[PDB]
Length: 49
Length: 39
Ligand SMILES: *[C@@H]1O[C@H](CO)[C@@H](O)[C@H](O)[C@H]1NC(C)=O
Image (tube, rainbow over all chains, first blue to last red; front, top):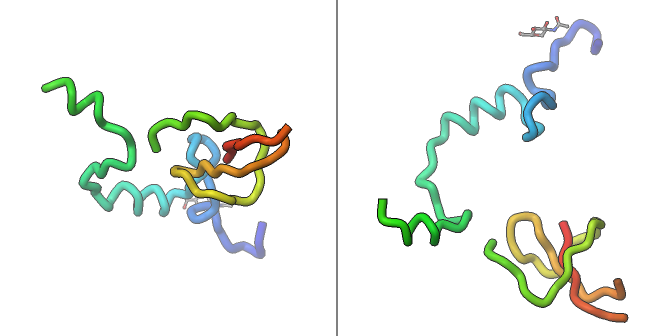
């Protein structure tokens, strides 16, 4: 309760293991990535699929 | 960021000293005197 102001859509939602809000989830889902190599991908590059 | 040989992980948290990768930092601490890695 913050005087009737609703902050539940920008405060974190701890239901998921990444403590992110709803609007932050939309922002992270809308920006599509090029799948950069910041996570290792040598095993996937070795296995020719 | 790959894997690290020669530094032992600790279940603590300090300020970053040597940045390694995705949240992992390394330092030269006493827990003897050796290189440790942490979050
Ligand atoms: C805040 O908004 C959400 C969705 O817009 C709603 O589910 C929630 O009940 C609201 N909070 C309060 C205290 O009514």
